[PDB]
Image (cartoon, grey):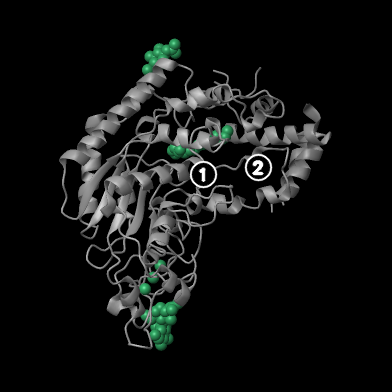
Amino acid sequence: QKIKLAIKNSVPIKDVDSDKYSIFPTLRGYHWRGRDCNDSDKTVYPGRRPDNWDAHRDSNCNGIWGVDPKDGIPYEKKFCEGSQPRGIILLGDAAGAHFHIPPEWLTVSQMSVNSFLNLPTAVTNELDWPQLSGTTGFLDSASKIKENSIYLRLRKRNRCNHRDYQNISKNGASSRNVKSLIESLSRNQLLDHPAIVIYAMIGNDVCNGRKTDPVSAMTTPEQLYANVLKMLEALNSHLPTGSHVILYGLAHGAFLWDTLHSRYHPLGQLNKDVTYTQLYSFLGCLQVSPCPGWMSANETLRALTSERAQQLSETLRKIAASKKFTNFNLFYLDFAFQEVVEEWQKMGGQPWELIEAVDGFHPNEVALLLFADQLWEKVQRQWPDVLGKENPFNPQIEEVFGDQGGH
Amino acid sequence: HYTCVGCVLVVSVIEQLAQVHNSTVQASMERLCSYLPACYMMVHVFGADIIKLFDNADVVCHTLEFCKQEPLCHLYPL
Ligand SMILES: *[C@@H]1O[C@H](CO)[C@@H](O[C@@H]2O[C@H](CO)[C@@H](O)[C@H](O)[C@H]2NC(C)=O)[C@H](O)[C@H]1NC(C)=O
Ligand SMILES: *[C@@H]1O[C@H](CO)[C@@H](O)[C@H](O)[C@H]1NC(C)=O
Ligand SMILES: [Ca+2]
Ligand SMILES: [Ca+2]
Ligand SMILES: [Ca+2]
């Protein structure tokens, strides 16, 4: 059935008007993109420019609409006319989507009834948790961390951007298949607000080759260059003028082995008989390793993997320096891994606390929000236009429209 | 493929549940079913004839035909 189509194309299954925004949380629904405030109208969706300033209805789902009874001005004109709204879009991989298997599942120690309360949600989100991710999370982090996602920082900044997030990330995404993800991106070049796009394929280009020679399976600089260029041409024909595109470099995954190779996996904390070295070897034996290159005990193979990853980052940096586009400007950011570690030690944490316990590979919720924190502060200093201005009408919008309909 | 990983993972929480609850595999296997919001059509029944009596997860999943062997993949030290 066409259910298969929605998941292969990473679009919601529950979406009557087929505008890619849902009233259903999971199955690529509003956990991934702003909730559709009218799933019966294809011309009502987050990110849209207001039709007649939403004097009669809320057409861009930011909760602002109607008219001020005093002067007959539409509220969205009084509160958003010059604030330069913009959306946040993530074109990412498993880390961008916040892949996460809760330790509470595999730990017999606490296997309470409350420990499996979140399972059908996780499974319907492909074990991803975009609603808690660093770029597009909107639910409160129940993790004792008061950092905010990039989207919530954009909303807090300008309450007109309410609900204008899109997490277009797929677990196995890379430069090799990003063309499919861009088809599922929603933006009308002439009818919607501009957007910030973060391209964050932080490892899959070097983390395939499960049944082959790992190095021979990795993306070459030439391949990635052509893939990303075609990627950017596509974006240029979808993104309203005045958008912004950030290319994120690849991760420094040598960190994984060094940090965990002799730490106890949660399935071995009780009996003390399992380490990540064992986990890495077990999954490598089964040819199901999420990253053979970096999860190896063979430190030459790990060195070749980091070298390729660094070579691919410099390719992305070269593209951001020498290519221009009419509808967006283009930037490059390094993987702020080192800066994330310094900031995390100050908070009394240790490095191994920044990696998913179960898979020992993806950054966890804590690290992602720290990566968002570093990106937000760095974009401010260098490229202030990318994030826009603070909107003086946040309290007033707050007083007229409350939660602005929620999420 | 993942059936070996999943089996080893499933079988490893069952066996780590009997060790935690000082019970048999039949007791843990049934108990596990109580945690998922009704697998007892298989486990209270289908797993009884198959499970408790024979007794780690690598052996079971290798014994249960879930980890085909044609390198011997094992999560726990042999
Ligand atoms: C979504 O918009 C549609 C109209 O585009 C709304 O449905 C119609 O609303 C008119 C009045 O505006 C009624 O006379 C019709 O009977 C409604 N139904 C149809 C099929 O046209 C609908 O109410 C809006 N949804 C929400 C949640 O506000
Ligand atoms: C390390 O990995 C490389 C693959 O790039 C392989 O050629 C080499 O033989 C490996 N060495 C050891 C000791 O496993
Ligand atoms: Ca709609
Ligand atoms: Ca819709
Ligand atoms: Ca509006």
Mark earlier in primary sequence (1, 2): 2
Picture residue at 49% right of the left edge, 54% below the top: A131
Could one spot residue A199 in this view of the protein? yes
Give coordinates of residue A156: x percent, y percent: 42, 60
Q: Which residue is mark 1?
A: A365
* Chain for disc number 1: A
Give coordinates of residue B18: x percent, y percent: 79, 34
Circles 1 and 2: CB distance less than 8 Å? no
Left or right? Give the position of B27 relative to A378. right
Query: Type of residue at label 2?
Result: Glu
Mark 1 and mark 2: span between their CA atoms?
Answer: 15 Å
Q: Which residue is mark 2?
A: A104
Quadrant housing residue A201:
top left
Residue A12 position (above or below residue A179): below
Residue A380 position (above or below residue A72): above
